[PDB]
Image 1 (spheres, rainbow, N blue to C red):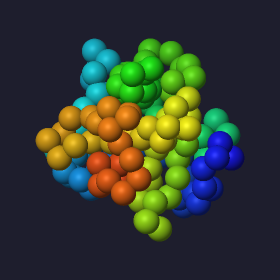
Image 2 (tube, rainbow, N blue to C red):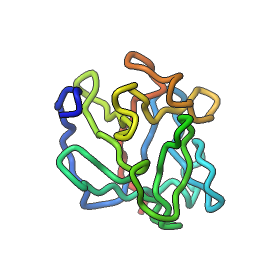
Image 3 (cartoon, rainbow, N blue to C red):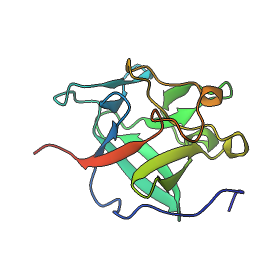
Length: 144
């Protein structure tokens, strides 16, 4: 189990979702240029994400607008990848019996999470850790 707990969130991957971070209220965003950050603008066309399970509890998070995959690099920075690779897999887990957290599969032994600061900037892998609000997400339905 990668030396991590296995409490999984409910919900499925049938439809795209917005990944809302409760820390600052930002939605995760992957720009066509590959930069990742968060925005409070719900009309943004780069916050609609499609998650898919490659194994139970292991997901890819892809921009539905650009087809890019969320990934975390060797130095802990999130970026949008044009193709799927080992840096694009995340262990999706329930947290505080309510939220979803995403731990980098490649860097799971160091507990590097996907996280957004209150100012909307992504947190670097080593700066994240259990207990922070930056790592707590709620997958919300995409607007209609």
